[PDB]
Amino acid sequence: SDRVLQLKLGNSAIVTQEAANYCCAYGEWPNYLPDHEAVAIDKPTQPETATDRFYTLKSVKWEAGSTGWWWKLPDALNNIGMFGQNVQHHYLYRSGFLIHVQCNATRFHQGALLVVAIPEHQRGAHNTNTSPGFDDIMKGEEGGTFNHPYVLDDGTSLACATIFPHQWINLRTNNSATIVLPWMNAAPMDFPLRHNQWTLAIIPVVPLGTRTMSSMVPITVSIAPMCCEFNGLRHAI
Amino acid sequence: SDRVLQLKLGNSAIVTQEAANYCCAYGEWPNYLPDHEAVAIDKPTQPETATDRFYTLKSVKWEAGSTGWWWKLPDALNNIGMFGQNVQHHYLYRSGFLIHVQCNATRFHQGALLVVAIPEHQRGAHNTNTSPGFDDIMKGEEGGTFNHPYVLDDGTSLACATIFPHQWINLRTNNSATIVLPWMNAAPMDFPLRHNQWTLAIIPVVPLGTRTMSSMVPITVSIAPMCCEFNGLRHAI
Amino acid sequence: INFYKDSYAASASKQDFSQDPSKFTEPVVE
Amino acid sequence: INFYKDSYAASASKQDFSQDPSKFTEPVVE
Amino acid sequence: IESIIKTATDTVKSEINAELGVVSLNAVETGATSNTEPEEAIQTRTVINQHGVSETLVENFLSRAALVSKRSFEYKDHTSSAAQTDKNFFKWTINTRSFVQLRRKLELFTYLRFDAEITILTTVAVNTYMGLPNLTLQAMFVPTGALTPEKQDSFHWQSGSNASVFFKISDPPARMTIPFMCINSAYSVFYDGFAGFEKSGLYGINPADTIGNLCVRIVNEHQPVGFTVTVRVYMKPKHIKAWAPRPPRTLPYMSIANANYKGKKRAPNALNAIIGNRDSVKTMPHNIVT
Amino acid sequence: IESIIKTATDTVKSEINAELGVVSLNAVETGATSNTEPEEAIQTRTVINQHGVSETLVENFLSRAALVSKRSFEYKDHTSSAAQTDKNFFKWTINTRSFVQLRRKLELFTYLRFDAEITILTTVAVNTYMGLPNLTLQAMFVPTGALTPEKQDSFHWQSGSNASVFFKISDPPARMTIPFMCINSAYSVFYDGFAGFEKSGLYGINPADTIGNLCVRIVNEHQPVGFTVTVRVYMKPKHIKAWAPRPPRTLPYMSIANANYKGKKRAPNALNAIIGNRDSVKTMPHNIVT
Amino acid sequence: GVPTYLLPGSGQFLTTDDHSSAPVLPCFNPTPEMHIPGQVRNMLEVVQVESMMEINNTESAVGMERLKVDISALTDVDQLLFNIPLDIQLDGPLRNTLVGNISRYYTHWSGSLEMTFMFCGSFMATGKLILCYTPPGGSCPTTRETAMLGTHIVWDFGLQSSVTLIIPWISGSHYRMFNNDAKSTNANVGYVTCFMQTNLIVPSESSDTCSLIGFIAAKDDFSLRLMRDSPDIGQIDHLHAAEAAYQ
Amino acid sequence: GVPTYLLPGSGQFLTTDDHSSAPVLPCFNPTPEMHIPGQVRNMLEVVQVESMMEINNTESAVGMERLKVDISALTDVDQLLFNIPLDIQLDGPLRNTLVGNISRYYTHWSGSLEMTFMFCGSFMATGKLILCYTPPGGSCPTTRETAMLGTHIVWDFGLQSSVTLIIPWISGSHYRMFNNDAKSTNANVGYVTCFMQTNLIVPSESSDTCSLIGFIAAKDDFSLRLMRDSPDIGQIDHLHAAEAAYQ
Amino acid sequence: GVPTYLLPGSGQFLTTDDHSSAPVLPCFNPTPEMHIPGQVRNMLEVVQVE
Amino acid sequence: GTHIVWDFGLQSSVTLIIPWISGSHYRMFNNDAKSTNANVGYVTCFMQT
Ligand SMILES: CC(=O)N[C@@H]1[C@@H](O)[C@H](O[C@@H]2O[C@H](CO[C@]3(C(=O)O)C[C@H](O)[C@@H](NC(C)=O)[C@H]([C@H](O)[C@H](O)CO)O3)[C@H](O)[C@H](O)[C@H]2O)[C@@H](CO)O[C@H]1O
Ligand SMILES: CC(=O)N[C@@H]1[C@@H](O)[C@H](O[C@@H]2O[C@H](CO[C@]3(C(=O)O)C[C@H](O)[C@@H](NC(C)=O)[C@H]([C@H](O)[C@H](O)CO)O3)[C@H](O)[C@H](O)[C@H]2O)[C@@H](CO)O[C@H]1O
């Protein structure tokens, strides 16, 4: 009941069947921006199935000395599909996200994945007073790697990161995490190229371990934007 | 509908037919001074058609290096007709104005006239600390010429002078401006020889230009005082 | 609050939300 | 007590006892 | 049509227009501003706009307490000082034109009717240091043209009928409301004429619009040492009615007696160039580099 | 389900359970916290729990007046002082990040909407002693990026439209409420991005979340002796709405511009050891000796 | 008597406080209110009046020449004529406007702008322009096919001396703010550009160069917050005759 | 006027006072409230979210290794695996938790705690643990038959990745207090111990060492009183760029 | 007690203020008003006499 | 394009619906594989993990 899950958005579908009951972030489902919260007065484009569909990223190799992986949203998707084209042709952006993180292994493998969506993950740099630059933050579809995931690369803590919307991929129990993110910003819409509302963080709290045949175990991230709005149509940036 | 216009006051009439829908200053039509605003207790003379009639001034030559023209009211009319005689024989004065500014040219001429009625146009002098004298301000029927019309000769701006009651004479569109001015003073009546409630300013924002046969293009100002009251009858000053 | 006997003594009157911008934006007759 | 004309001027509002901890403790759907 | 506006207007959703008849194209030459709505220009959404408009109320825009007078004088023995010096007292004809932030705000209008809330801050500095005296000052309101005192211990300071306020430096600042005083229903912020029957009077200055005089002394006899006493007068207009808005002052003010202008030497706010220059009309001044 | 909670919950008595079916064993991997009640884990009694929960209200947890700025400067003649020195005046861009007790409390949340109650304490020390002057200070609120004064007797201190507060050292501390000012519905306590359209802007700093500027001068002319004047600014957030709680800061703060981290050299709060070490996982750190 | 205690903020003079204060003249009867034309109750009434943009803020454009843009016949198609920077809180073609000068008493602003352009050629002058508003993000568009992807109006100035380009309020935030940073995502409004949609086509006896006067107003969805001193006026001295007020 | 007298406490600035104060900006209209997800009205909402205990707070456990307890197959029965000190007001495995960090802004605390342990071996890993809460009084129990006399849960982690050990509020007083004295009868909560109830029994191709992640939350009978500065953050200098706020 | 704050103008003596002040003689009974001819209530009564 | 993501852990089967997405009511054989009236597009399979 909690394991079986079917996720159809647009022309994309995902059947995960070793799932663990999906996370709706703060009990909030994505919606379109209502008229009493709206600011930009032009009629938005809501591309629906052209953008509200699962975008699979490049898989990362879960390895023995791995620290963690992060992707920033919408930045991981700003150059993919018709979502990326609506991002590049519009000033404003608003959507929710359906994040589906996939990692299976054998029944002889051990390993726990904290799959956590962090709102406004302002990254700190280590051992310096200089703030992280544009290239450290805006990695795009490739994402980044955690430097010190124990303090979540911001001087706080991995241990208290369960205050954020999260699931776990414990290789005993499940092979997929599913987080549903709403719009998470102080503003109604946003310029999607200079601001990230959510950071999907995927962290090896318990490392991958087995004594069976060593296979490449990947972690696959599929992200569906949900309820996309785009205001301020112009030329492509 | 907006172009055709017929202006009958007293024995004077004006048919303009390339007009652009007349300006009533601040949405206010001239009236006589009511009893609840009246101050001077003698019965005023209201000469009606003897004064409430169009007074045409001397025309000015719209030329290539022209800066602008101004006339101060009632000072431009204080020596004309029966309006001037009622001004010279009475201490107090109150009227509105119907200003009709006339300038036509060919369909090959270009040029824009900001025709603007400025309330309390306290003129500044340029490049000095000395205030303008009586001879700089009180020009009478001849009027004056703008020195620096870009700052309206008072250190402000031509560009924001559309906050005042104005029309334009764009030689494409129209050949006449029509501004209806009410009484515009902090006091109910006024001594008409030392105070000007309105200044008609006429300014070449776009200069006169053509490549056809060069003719003298004049700007003709016809001003009708409206709802004249005169208190404090005495000898002629 | 005003305990003075003159009405001009009172605090500022920041309550007049009546606007008529059309006397400056549309001072036309037709 | 507030004698200022702006509502932000008032004292702190220590009266909101509404809790929804389940949006952090049970953000699940089933 | 006059209406009560507390928030900015809502945007209604709009659709595709393709109509042969009624018009984004207006008539400038009538002097009217464009009534083109965004619903008629682009295809809009519904926006319920909850943005308040109260901070641009003329009452809020002008009821800021602004510095109108700032006078330092020596508080000392003035047996052997010059006849120009403020000898423990100054007089000040109340104007709104000496300090340019309040001046440009009030000169946004042609006519103003307001009560003048007058706040008086006094600071004292020793001219070695032995401490600051808690001095009593007298500020006496004197009408325009009336008799002002000529020395510190003048018998005009008795204030049989002039309003005087006594206040100490350790106290909060002295605060009085001067009413709307004009013989007219509004002050003339600009006065296009002479306020005298001969042709030698001052242009632009109507003494009806002068509030009056602040005659400010130190009530104390002088100390054995000298002090510099700076009196700052603050005016907050209140119960404000404003009429006939004007173009704002662009050029720097030259004088308080008139609207004379010079401009700055270069753009911005020069005589022939109010806005700072760009290279061409197709040069974008802060173009985003990508 | 959202509900009003004024006291901690009561415990109901419970009995012996021996059931084959419904479960003390939950699902961590869903991201949900354990809903196991003590009634279901042990055999409980009835406790009517009257413990209030009002002190952990976010309004009470954050409406403490906290030191946000502490600036000393010389109050003296500054004819021959360095161009770095505060020459009888300082400006301060209002931040909540310079003092770490308030910073960590506000950084417990992602979004905060609050009005800022600003309290200003001024202390003065003589730089021999002759007494302390009751000085008047001006604190002028200036918006983010706007013009701040450049000297003590600047004409920007006239405050035609800037709010200024004048206050004396002998008075109670100056106190103003700054509203919730942000162009957004909340401040972003953390800002994951750049607030500029080019790629050279600052990371983590949204100027929408900057309250503004406190420009604090001494209004007095300088005395013949010098004084050290320490201005302490206190901010109490009020009418607080807080969104999206975060892990608390564990490592020491390095800067106010960012969330950079170093940790301490050893546990506790080191980069690789937040909690202080014990000898083994089966070593009890404060074991009772009997 | 009444047990009281003084709060923090006792004795302070906040210049924005709102209190009753002592009447200097008791039983003074102010002069009766007379109706005066043109009463302003809210500064947004002024801000909605269209006023001339100084689009030609270039050198050699002297005084009044700065308030018009001369357009000429071109021999290449799709050509850029002028552009306008759009931050009303900054110095530029919008600053000395009624919307610009009142807004620079404020820090925060919301709401749509209207741009009205009056064509001031001859009656015989014909032509089509395209007036494009580009929402912010990248550089200002320099070609016509890039700028018409944004908000635009196409204007035949044959019989029509004027059009309005509504610059709609398209912002992420409820307000845009001044912070002395033109390129800020909280500040930058984007761009207005004008292109030859066809060509300025005049006969031989019309003047071959024609002028455009541009206006800007605010709409009635416009708002201004956070009142500040204006950067448009200033002093570093006392004015002339200000000492005479003390004499 | 009104006869008044000033009380003691007049003119003082208590940082916890609760008064209205003067608006710096009159008629300021704040930005409209928008719904934002995840509003917290009371800090006990945060404190009930389970967060990782750092039970492996030992040397050689570096960073993330501190957030898991490695359990191995043992060849003796009833063996102790780990223990946890229980004072949430102190430094230890509970300090950098959501219940621990918020509680150390407070001095007094009441209410039950829950400990959730997630087993992170392989699917093929089987075994039974006993998680014992011992109420305070004597030393921490070192043998299994001593610790199971207290509150315990017995957990087969065969199909069951998680259990909860409720640490029930068992105190003489309504609250427990921090006073920097761990052994105080007003402070000490007792002990959590874990024992092999059977054995961690894995096949040859599972990893022979398995990890446990421990969580702690507070329950909804939890309360916090007496707000204090946190001992978890501090400074002895000004931070970097804090001087730049004055420039 | 009552939380108060002093306004600007606290402690000032405006000679045209209008306040009650402390009775120097408590329970003093003033002499009964007798009708006297020629009472003036407003100075404009005097000003209208030629 | 149109896709299904399939964990074959407990699930021996999935279905990829190839939906009828054509300009015309029918697709025709004409011995021309690259014809716009004939070509249906592609099915591909990738390692998702
Ligand atoms: C401060 C900053 O980020 N950049 C400065 C540039 O803006 C500056 O370039 C000059 O900027 C000038 C700005 O125009 C105003 C303004 O601040 O809005 C226009 C005001 O009306 C004017 N005020 C008065 C009373 O005249 C004001 C004033 O002149 C300046 O504050 C004086 O410094 O300027 C304007 O556009 C200039 O044309 C432009 O060159 C550069 C200098 O090149 O300095 C940067 O620090
Ligand atoms: C005061 C007392 O009764 N005993 C002291 C011992 O506790 C101390 O042993 C050290 O104690 C440390 C305590 O941990 C904290 C704390 O006070 O809770 C953890 C805080 O997060 C940390 N704060 C910051 C800003 O980093 C705080 C801080 O480091 C200390 O106050 C600095 O002194 O410590 C911790 O567990 C250590 O690992 C432990 O050795 C001994 C010294 O051995 O001194 C006793 O006086």
Image (spheres, coloured by chain):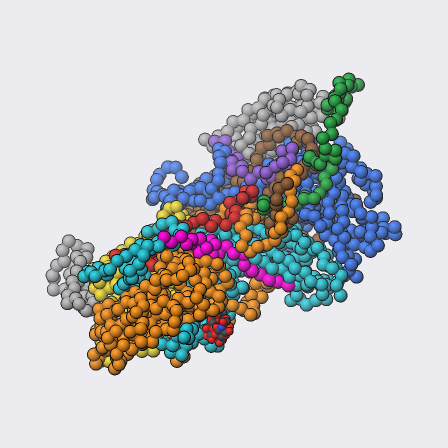
Chain colours: A yellow, C purple, D red, E blue, F cyan, G brown, H orange, I green
Residue E179, image x, y percentages: 67, 36
Residue G119, image x, y percentages: 49, 45
**Quadrant hosting residue A98:** bottom left
Q: Nearer the viewer, residue H9 or A14?
A: H9
- Tell me which residue sits at (36%, 50%) in the image: F3
Residue E180, image x, y percentages: 66, 35
**Quadrant hosting residue H85:** bottom left
Residue E2's place in the image compared with F77, above or below, is above
- Tell me which residue sits at (62%, 42%) in the image: G2
Left or right: F13 as drawn, with respect to E210? left
| The C terminus of chain E, quarter of image | bottom left
Left or right: A12 as drawn, with respect to E241? left
Number of labelled discs? 0
**Quadrant hosting residue A190:** bottom left
Query: Taking the image as drawn, is residue G7 in sight?
Result: yes
- Tell me which residue sits at (64%, 47%) in the image: H6
Is residue A12 highlighted in magenta? no
Question: In this view, which residue lies farthest toward the bottom?
Answer: H75
- Residue extent of the magenta highlight: F48-72
- Tell me which residue sits at (74%, 59%) in the image: F131
